[PDB]
Image 1 (tube, chains in turn yellow, blue):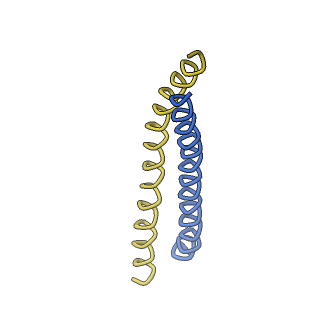
Image 2 (cartoon, each protein chain N blue to C red):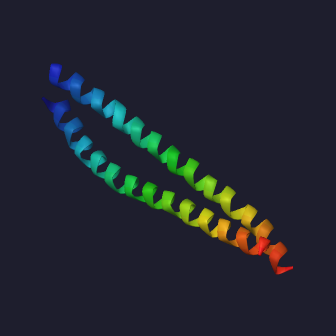
Length: 48
Length: 48
C-alpha cells in the first residue's frame, strides 16, 4: 500500500511528460519536412 | 500484490517508450541535419 502510492504518483507525472515530449517530437519532425521541401525547391532553381 | 505488478509493468513500458520516442526525434532531427547540410552544397553552388 505504500509502494503503490509512490509508483502511481510517479506514473501520473511521467505520463504527463509523455504529452510534452511527444509534442516536441512531432514539432521536431515537421522541421525536417519543411527542410526538404525547401531543399527541393532550391534544387529546382539550380536546374532553372 | 496483483495491483503492484500491473502498475510496475506499465511503468516499465512507458519509461522505456519515452526513451523509445526520444530516440525517434533524435533519429528525426539527425535526418534534418542530413537534409540541411547537403542543401548548402547546392546553395553555395548556385550562389557561385
